[PDB]
Structures are given as C-alpha cells and as structure tokens.
Image: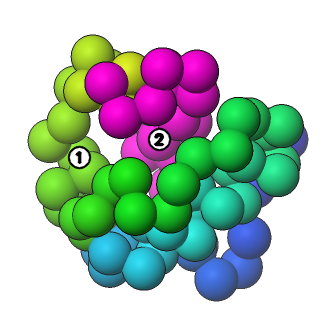
Amino acid sequence: SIALPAHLRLQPIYWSRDDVAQWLKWAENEFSLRPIDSNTFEMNGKALLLLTKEDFRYRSPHSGDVLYELLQHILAQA
C-alpha cells in the first residue's frame, strides 16, 4: 500500500509551504521521479489544491501528472 510518512499524515489542505516541499522530496524517492526543484511549488496545501493536472504538468513536464494522481489518491484517504 501507499502510506505517507508519519510527518505528513495530515489532510493536504493543512500542509504548509514546507510540508509541500517535504512531500515533493518524498514522492521523488518513493516513486523514482525526476529531480524536481524544491522551490517549484512555492505555496501551501490549500493552494496546491487549486492547481489543475495541466498546471502540475506545467511545473514539472516529467513528474507532473504523477504528482497530481498521488495527491488525488491522498485526498481519497481518511
């Protein structure tokens, strides 16, 4: 199964700008994604939630849609 590390176990809506950077750092190792600059999503979880799939793909051509589905999958948790 796909379980978030203990430090990020809260609903994304509550992630701070630094939780976002920490989720990107984790996803990259966990999922073997391309290197993704940490200052790529300079925003918090609330703002992260407004972005479309197209937007994620804009910020990251390679990882883009994977980071999006991971987030959707996380939202469907609880």
| Secondary structure beneath label 2 | helix
Q: Is residue 49 above or below residue 11?
A: above
**Residue at screen point 74% across, 70% down:** 5
Q: Which residue is denoted by mark 2 in the rendering?
A: 71
The image position of residue 18, as x and y in percent, is 42, 79
* Disc 2 to disc 1: CB gap under 8 Å: yes
Distance from Cα at disc 2 to Cα at disc 1: 9 Å
Q: Is residue 59 above or below residue 65?
A: below
Q: Is residue 35 left or right of residue 18?
A: right
The disc, 2 or 1, on the residue closer to the chain's N-terminal end is 1
* Residue at image location 23% in from the left, 46% down from the top: 49
- Residue beneath the point at 14% across and 41% down: 50
Q: Is 62 within the magenta?
A: yes
Tag 1 residue: 49
Instruction: Using a 10 Å C-alpha cutoff, classify the residue at mark 2 as few (fewer than 14 neighbours), some (14 to 19) or many (20 or more).
Output: some
Give the amino acid at mark 2. Answer: Leu
Q: Quadrant of the N terminus?
A: top right
The answer to which of 60 and 50 lies nearer the viewer is 60
Tell me the element at label 1.
loop
Q: Position of residue 23 (x, y in %)?
A: 57, 62
Relative placement, left or right, of 13 versus 67 is: left
Q: Is residue 25 above or below residue 71?
A: below
Image quadrant in which you'd find residue 20: bottom left
Q: Residues within 10 Å of mark 1 (few under 14, many from 20)?
A: some
The rendered magenta stretch, by its main secondary structure, is classed as helix
- Residue range (magenta): 58-78
**One can see residue 62 in this view:** yes
Q: Nearer the viewer, residue 62 or 11?
A: 62
Q: What is the quadrant of residue 9 in the picture?
A: bottom right
Please state the horizontal and vertical placement of residue 77, each as a whole percent of the image. Answer: 53, 47
User: Where in the figure is residue 10, as x and y percent of width and height?
Assistant: 47, 73
